[PDB]
Image (cartoon, rainbow over all chains, first blue to last red):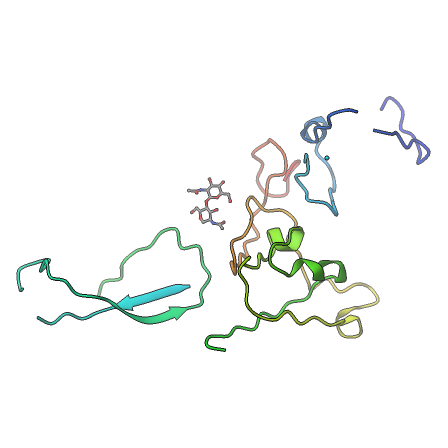
Length: 42
Length: 43
Length: 96
Ligand SMILES: *[C@@H]1O[C@H](CO)[C@@H](O[C@@H]2O[C@H](CO)[C@@H](O)[C@H](O)[C@H]2NC(C)=O)[C@H](O)[C@H]1NC(C)=O
């Protein structure tokens, strides 16, 4: 984001979602997931 | 399960006999290791 | 019985349903896969009074990342770093 938003910015997601791009954007300090960690699979 | 079956065949001195024999179960150790590779142990 | 084994472990309540043949999730997939052809008994009880601590009991560890699923009765206690991204990093890493 150009400027970070507070919790109000709950953005709704008809788009294919690729989660590897998120790892391509930046490394993460922490990453937890109740769902399986690789994910990218409706 | 590391299943070990064996037979001692004290009968054909020179090499593989070509004889028909059968192995008997001995033990089925519950180790649970993937064991992709193995090696021998010599004295 | 003929040859009987008793497997002892601690899980979360929401994971009790995963210790059964055919189940998936972080436990069935990455900690212990139970065979689909399974004969035996799964006995579970609440241990909040024994295992929990006010500050949090961190002695119990759950595997969250692995490169493949486990086979029946397989155990793997390796702590080698797993790469979650595309970079082949070592040690604690940007995508490790
Ligand atoms: C048993 O060992 C083999 C290798 O000795 C494992 O196969 C490897 O699995 C990883 C992913 O977990 C792959 O990235 C490698 O390319 C595989 N190599 C080979 C030669 O197959 C196998 O996964 C192990 N068994 C289990 C249940 O993990």
